Amino acid sequence: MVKSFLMLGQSNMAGRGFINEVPMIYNERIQMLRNGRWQMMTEPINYDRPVSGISLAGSFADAWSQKNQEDIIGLIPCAEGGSSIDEWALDGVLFRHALTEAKFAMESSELTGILWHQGESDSLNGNYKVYYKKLLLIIEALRKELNVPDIPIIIGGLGDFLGKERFGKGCTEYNFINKELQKFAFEQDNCYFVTASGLTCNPDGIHIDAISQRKFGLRYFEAFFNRKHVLEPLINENELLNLNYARTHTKAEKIYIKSMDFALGKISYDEFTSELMKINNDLE
Amino acid sequence: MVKSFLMLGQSNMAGRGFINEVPMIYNERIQMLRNGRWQMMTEPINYDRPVSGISLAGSFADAWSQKNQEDIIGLIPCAEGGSSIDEWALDGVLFRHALTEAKFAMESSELTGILWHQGESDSLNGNYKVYYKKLLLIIEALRKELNVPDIPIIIGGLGDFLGKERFGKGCTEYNFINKELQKFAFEQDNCYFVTASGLTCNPDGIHIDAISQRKFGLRYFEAFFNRKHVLEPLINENELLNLNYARTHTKAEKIYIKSMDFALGKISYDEFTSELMKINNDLE
Image (cartoon, rainbow over all chains, first blue to last red; front, side):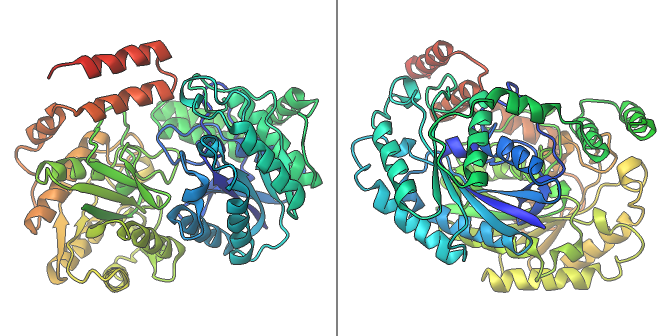
């Protein structure tokens, strides 16, 4: 079947990594939800802004497909940039929209997990003193509404680069939010924390970069697959990624990158044809 | 207030024009729906595929903003590439998803019109003999469900390049669909037809190109604004477009193109700063 994963949070969940700084992930077994149905995943996955880029859900799915050669993983993009915990209130629009997206997804897939990452917009002037209780109502409503009382919900921490440079300089209370995120995970059932140590950011000083967003996805899967808290970065983080990048592509996959090259006008029709035949004639 | 317009149809409504072949439209008074709420419009508007590009809704909105300097126009992207009239059935997922999107939009805007363009996937082996009756049920359900019994619904024809080259060669019955589209418009209340004469296509032989997609948008507005059938192309089509391209941008707008240039890594932070001050210091 199709195992779907709901994506919730701020811009760091939707992904802002520069897609030209990390290798493309073309996995015919990884899919994204486009206006209610499944389509082959191609970053930007969570296109909430014209600037959406590399997400952590990319490597998460790639790593997931390697541990499950049989099924297909479906991603449900519902992250909103700049959104704060208050904007995610049950009565909220971006929460009720996430529900409708999830439901559309589960009428053709099975919701297996929920990926959450948010907190930059709450890393200032207190309001971290109410973050927990706020999150509890959101998670509670999610499990109830979507009828998933025990599926693992993974939550990541905030980058240590916050509260220092430009767009991120206003987030001086990020570490106070991390404590609430951690606490929430330990105390709440079926919730796991994922450290963001070592992760770096783009020039804006607030968004995690592509490279770091790729490692971040592995830690998310590491937590999900083993149902544990990832308090430290995985050791084979770099090599683990290259191992997925080296994977040989299917005929359908390499025909896809070519169909797209042509669709975007990057190559001629005859050049597209010649390239398609090479794939067809190729041995193995 | 915010006047919203629901976009329905196939890939030629979602837009597949190459964004690098036509000038960018940056209008702070034109917005798009991103996961339930309004955000400043930036093409691709209807991102249903990683290949989504220039849509006809772009120039439609630009022309609309010039005849209404007071309000803001909101676009609701709900077009699915490759979808056929059958996939748009009331019980369908991409129809029920369009409804939920429209409703989310109207709880913060007023649905003023519906833009429809579809039929390439029905331009083969008959089934054009059932297109009308099929469309009637879809339109009927839309007005009833969304409580908009008299808002103008505009429908465009199919390109004359269809049924001849590559990806479009299979659409040999396009002209039979056009007749049904036309008929439907004349007979049905508050429905207007928009010819696609003169419009050209990209190399794939099936998708209307950026230039043509821009002219196509004007004809849509021409029909909507005057509540009439556009059976011929507008005469000042080219100049009418340049007139909108020449428009001087607002301070907020030019600050936006700069905020994006930086957000995408196209410029340095200091270069971004320097550019922001120039905008601030500028006289008029």
